Amino acid sequence: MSGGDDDWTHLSSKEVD
Amino acid sequence: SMPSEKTFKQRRSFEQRVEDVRLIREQHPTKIPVIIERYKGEKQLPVLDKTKFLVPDHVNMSELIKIIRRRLQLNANQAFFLLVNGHSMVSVSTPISEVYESERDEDGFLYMVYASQETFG
C-alpha cells in the first residue's frame, strides 16, 4: 500500500549478497 | 553542473520534507532517514524502487550501498555509486547514524544521489 508514508523501505543487510 | 530542475531538497517543501520524517521519527526512531534519488540527468542506473529508505543505526554507510545494489538489482558488470550529499563515499569509516547527523540538515532527512558515475564532478 502506497496510500501514505506509513513506513518507508527497510534496509536489511541480511537480504544483501 | 549548471542545474536546471529543482532538487528533492529544494523542490519538495522543506516543512513537508521535515514532517515526512516526523513519521519515521515516531515510527522508526532507531532508523536513519535518507532520500536516495537518481542524479539529475541519470540515464544509466534505473529509477530506484523507492525514494525513502530506513537505514539501521547499527551499521556503516557502506551497508546502505550493498543495500541499494539489491534494490537496483544490477549485475556485477553494472557500475553503481551512491553519492552522499552529492559526494561519493570512497571512504566509509562512519556509521550511517553519524554520516546522517554529519550531513543531514535540520529537516532530518538525508539526501544522496546514486548513478553509474562516482567521478562525474
Image (cartoon, helix red, strand yellow):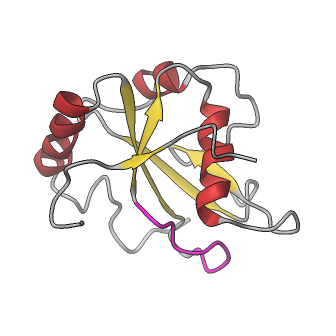
Magenta stretch contains residue B45: yes
Most frequent secondary structure within the magenta stretch: loop
For image coordinates 13% across by 50% down, the residue present is B16
The front one of B55 and B97 is B55
Q: Quadrant of the N terminus of chain B?
A: bottom right
Q: Residue furthest bottom?
A: B43
Q: Bounds of the magenta span?
A: B42-50
Q: Position of residue B121 (x, y in %)?
A: 68, 56
The picture quadrant where one finds residue B89 is top right
A9 vs B23, left or right, is right
Q: How many marks?
A: 0
B13 vs B75, left or right, is left
The front one of B78 and B44 is B78
Magenta stretch contains residue B39: no
Q: Position of residue B80 (x, y in %)?
A: 72, 59
Q: Position of residue B52 (x, y in %)?
A: 37, 52
The front one of A13 and B43 is A13
Q: Residue furthest right?
A: B77
A11 vs B12, left or right, is right
For image coordinates 72% across by 61% down, the residue present is B120
Q: Position of residue B68 (x, y in %)?
A: 60, 52
For image coordinates 76% across by 37% down, the residue present is B90
Up/down of B45 relative to A17, above or below: below
Up/down of B53 relative to B73, above or below: above
For image coordinates 31% across by 52% down, the residue present is B9
